[PDB]
Amino acid sequence: KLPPGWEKAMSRSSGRVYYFNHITNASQWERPSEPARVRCSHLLVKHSQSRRPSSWRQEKITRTKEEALELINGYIQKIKSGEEDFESLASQFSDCSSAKARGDLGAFSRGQMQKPFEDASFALRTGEMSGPVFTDSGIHIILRTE
Ligand SMILES: N=C(N)NCCC[C@H](NC(=O)[C@@H]1CCC/C1=C/[C@H](COP(=O)(O)O)NC=O)C(N)=O
Image 1 (cartoon, rainbow, N blue to C red):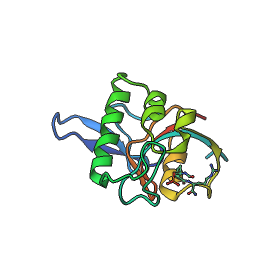
Image 2 (image 1 turned 60 degrees about the vertical axis):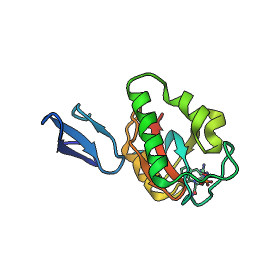
Image 3 (image 1 turned 90 degrees about the horizontal axis):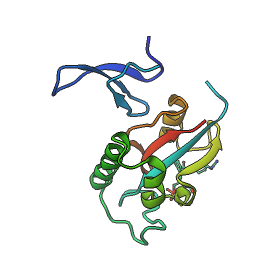
């Protein structure tokens, strides 16, 4: 009957059905198939409207929300085609401190992370990746590892 968050959608360019998750922003052709804690890695792209417009990559972050989203889109594209792996992109490009640990955040339960991240994280199954997930930090790609 489809896991939490998943809905059937119709492709504009091909007419083929696909599946979309409105919690994680994941989308795929394939038909998809709770814990106390999950472990996730993430790649963060911050923007001018981030709660802290600063990171290890640059002192003053000034890119716009729309620009950050386009970077996130491009990374997802490289991950999905296997041009670059997630961990590699997070180490190089995530505006989070967890970049030094390949995006890994360790384990966490509900009530610890900003709500959109948390919900997305818990709706992923082990091994799955999110689409763009928006929080006050910026835009995330989430990978559930455990
Ligand atoms: N148990 C653990 N590890 N502590 C959870 C408490 C921190 C938590 N953080 C976040 O929710 C954002 C979203 C997902 C990752 C994340 C990372 C942020 C991003 O960097 P910032 O926007 O702050 O500059 N870094 C936090 O220092 C929060 N309640 O604000």
